[PDB]
Image (tube, rainbow, N blue to C red; front, side, top):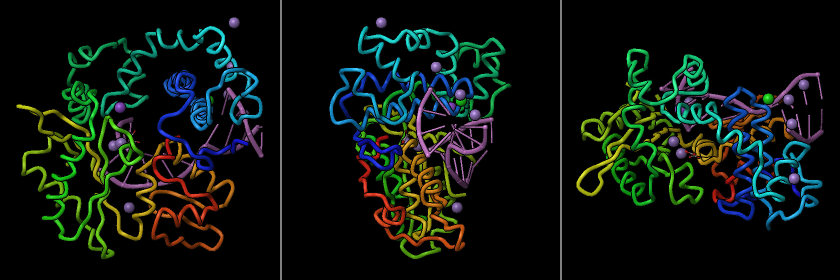
Length: 327
DNA sequence: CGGCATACG
DNA sequence: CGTA
DNA sequence: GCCG
Ligand SMILES: O=C([O-])C(=O)[O-]
Ligand SMILES: [Cl-]
Ligand SMILES: [Mn+2]
Ligand SMILES: [Mn+2]
Ligand SMILES: [Mn+2]
Ligand SMILES: [Mn+2]
Ligand SMILES: [Mn+2]
Ligand SMILES: [Mn+2]
Ligand SMILES: [Mn+2]
Ligand code: NA
């Protein structure tokens, strides 16, 4: 009925089990904060299964046979069905550890391992970090300086304005180069916390060296509040606002046209969808997938793809448009 | 039991 | 280590 | 935590 991999089923952005999936994703996030990547994956996959269902789960019976639902995740759902609340989920939500790790890892430049060390050192608030600035990287300094703006949702109106600015710099850097919106906005999201663009050129090889030229041109237009210094740039952009501006996270990626379908697939997401697609590729088809290509390790050859549709066909999967990849 | 995606900065 |  |  329900296939076991997220890449085998459509998952829309909005669905019929929002509250249940949100609770399982709390437990997934908490597992990640404790270094338990296996438990994180199971809770993420269980949440995703619910997102793919055609109607609301009303009774425990309806979980029988669903993949990734065992004793633990089924108990979470049963408590939510019976009481409207899962005691374990609420305990996590309320915990100082969860709240502080969430706060710290949401900083650009701070991962789980840094947040955990800071937690163990007794630090709890952003102002605690600002009081010891010499212990921060340039990237963390930027993430902390801009943290408030970076916590404010990006709207689709913002995205269209940013895309025009990036296109202008890309056109000067290399006439004929193209700019494609990726990430969650390509999956149909109306808001996000960052904007992603994928840049290529129709003539293989002409894109070499492009990203430095693009960044220099954005920087001299005064639009770059932060960048590293390549084929991936993780920036903070200055975005105009009524009578002011706000900081926005923007990722710029370059790929040659031979790699573009793979890069588009990977950068469009969702994260879980791509992990599941790569898992499926390797475990079920014996092929190795990343955002550069698809490798047959037995013949030692790369698959040529001209489209995302090609890639799904290579893997024997029915095609899913981006708006159904919201695993 | 082992596995859990796979890259770049 | 961080980032996607 | 769950799957094969
Ligand atoms: O930023 C994200 O979450 C994405 O683009 O999928
Ligand atoms: Cl684990
Ligand atoms: Mn348990
Ligand atoms: Mn009860
Ligand atoms: Mn994104
Ligand atoms: Mn991004
Ligand atoms: Mn590359
Ligand atoms: Mn084991
Ligand atoms: Mn375990
Ligand atoms: Na972070």
